[PDB]
Amino acid sequence: MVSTIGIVSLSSGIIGEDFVKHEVDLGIQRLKDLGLNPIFLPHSLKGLDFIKDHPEARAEDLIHAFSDDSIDMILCAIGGDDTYRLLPYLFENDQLQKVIKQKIFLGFSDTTMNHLMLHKLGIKTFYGQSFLADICELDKEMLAYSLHYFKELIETGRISEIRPSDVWYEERTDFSPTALGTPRVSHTNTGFDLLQGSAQFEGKILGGCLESLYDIFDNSRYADSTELCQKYKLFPDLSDWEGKILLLETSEEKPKPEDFKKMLLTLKDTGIFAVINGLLVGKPMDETFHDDYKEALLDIIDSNIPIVYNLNVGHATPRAIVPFGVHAHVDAQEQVILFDYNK
Ligand SMILES: Nc1ncnc2c1ncn2[C@@H]1O[C@H](COP(=O)(O)O)[C@@H](O)[C@H]1O
Image (cartoon, rainbow, N blue to C red; front, top):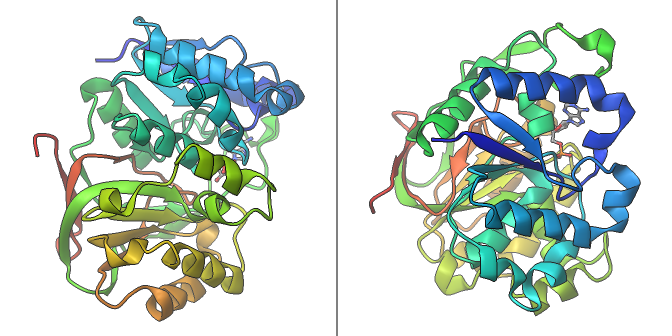
């Protein structure tokens, strides 16, 4: 299915920096070991400062990744917080539209913005893993659960189903060469947690990182985020959201409960909760504010919407891959999400 895999830095430029080189070289070797030919797009390794300063270079890399028929899959390096800045370089003169096609695209976090970009252009994408975060796992092997989904994707171009992991892991405090070959701290995973509504619900999934979506509507982080996202109509129409399942997950920022609440209400203000078929929420990173987020969801989300919490999707580890734009059936009782590529 996949032979050449192209690595893009569309958010932070970290993967080019000396201090992560040991991690990068490890992931490169793993991709090779999986039967892939990993290539870095021309600007992807230019480092933090260059990539921050040149969103146009990022856009160039993405356009090239889609345009180049030899590239079978696009893997995001890592998230960040400013990929919105690519919008004019992708959309002003239909630059991305001109080259766009159905090709595997995988990332999470700030990449949420890019997922919305690609959705706009009619592309089905894949949420929930990145090169640095998953492929460069510092233990001897990739996390088993994560690897299950990655290998499925590269072998079949699809994810058939998601089931909960048996365990979850803490985020590392040490990513230096010293950490090589050392294991993450493990916890028992208690599975999908049906907070409210029906245990069965269906629809195509779209969403990603709550913090990312919030910057569509709240210009605190970047003063022109809302302007750019409005100009380019990045947030889907409510007729588009109608009958979809929204995914939400929280980042390493670990918003305090009152800020989580403010984010959910800001989303509510879009009208999205009136039209969706259900809500999937990832386990918070490190389970930080796990209980508080649960309470906030129960307090705020419209009463008619089913909510499944504690998915192994997002910033906690290990990490499932979630197809976007593919009909899903969620069964909270049986603890499975099944995908139907024909629907
Ligand atoms: N050097 C690193 N190596 C591996 N994972 C990292 C590194 N830096 C950050 N992460 C993790 O990558 C995940 C996604 O980061 P981000 O895309 O920036 O939200 C988070 O859970 C981070 O803790």
